[PDB]
Image 1 (cartoon, helix red, strand yellow):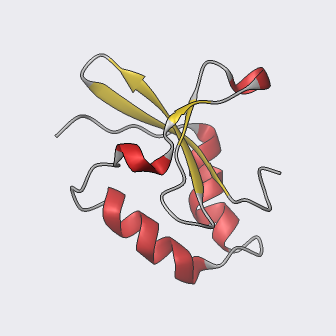
Image 2 (tube, helix red, strand yellow):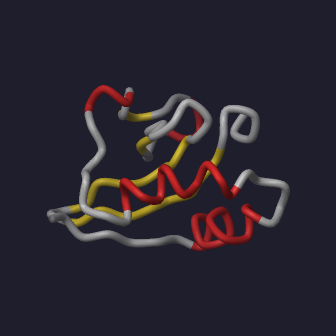
Length: 88
């Protein structure tokens, strides 16, 4: 499968967000699909965001999750993680 990466944002938005009042019980579901091998589906409204987040890609793996990442040459990179109530 494609390559995966992590940024300073995702690093603090993954484990540092869990203890920051984030439901770690829901992560086990999203982190289970990305940390296993199952790639994101096109039905997750995955595409370029609007505004200042133009040079990025969003994808709500769950109805309460919004993981941001970038598409590189035969390589993927994780940007950050948020929620419908967080990112908003």
